[PDB]
Image (cartoon, rainbow, N blue to C red; front, side, top):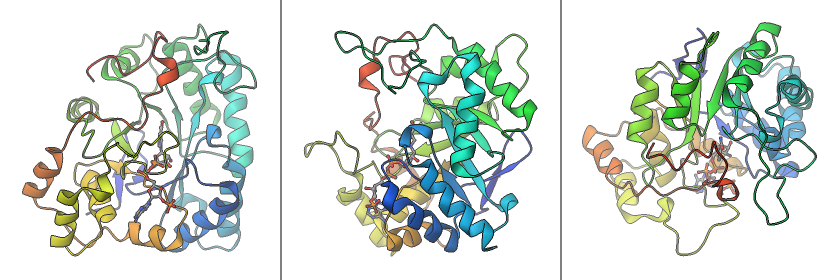
Length: 316
Ligand SMILES: NC(=O)c1ccc[n+]([C@@H]2O[C@H](COP(=O)([O-])OP(=O)(O)OC[C@H]3O[C@@H](n4cnc5c(N)ncnc54)[C@H](OP(=O)(O)O)[C@@H]3O)[C@@H](O)[C@H]2O)c1
């Protein structure tokens, strides 16, 4: 199937990207260089991952070496929660641009709907541990994002971890100038997201699936948690197709018209993970993988469950 999907800003986005959350700063430059060498043209980044400088070193060498042209790359980053204030959004975007060594981003996302007190700490907590919110609302933050488009710093803006009523709030914003191009959400066979995906797609919002392999390196993993990569039912589908389990887990969202961003710092897996355009899951296989849903989340933002904009109390 086609390697890019068209966004509602008129640009095309590669449906397979490289994730960089938890990629160590001393390994991610090589990981991104290898990814671009073996075909990746989309890199998913974020300021809160604390490795954008090192990602940028890789992008800049491959541009300098003329392995790729800037127009052929699709670089994504995300506004962290402590920068939702109007007077802080441009500088947060410009810090990311400087670190990535870019003059524009292809896509910039609000990382979470929850704004936090600005300061040095990414998770400012009170005298009892609760996240300290900011009195920013989603709509003024969105307006700040819209200005970034009008200043040329980003080609597209979007959202991440927004539930459907939060997406709706932006779509119904008075004076809305640019619709979100993307909602990036967790999605895999144990969290299949059928309701939120259908909502977003019905509105021409492209969905990106994060943690598609179930994030086995997540810092809070527990031996007793489910494991997609070890699920014998998914291994059997892989075996049937003579592919790896990870390749089946990456092809699965692709066939739902999603974008997907598997993370690896291992050269062999970076290359393996891109070899997903040569096979097809049947509709039966797709329905079977959807049947594994258990509403299980990797990323539940547990420190923020009382924030007014916490996204995961709503069904979807
Ligand atoms: N918007 C958000 O809030 C949000 C949240 C979470 C994630 N994300 C984005 O989504 C990306 C992907 O999600 P994720 O990092 O949580 O996890 P993931 O992509 O589901 O899983 C990454 C893990 O799987 C391993 N792996 C990769 N390929 C493999 C293969 N072929 N065989 C076996 N294991 C394999 C990696 O190991 P090695 O690296 O050691 O090879 C790493 O431990 C992130 O990196 C980030 O860019 C966004």
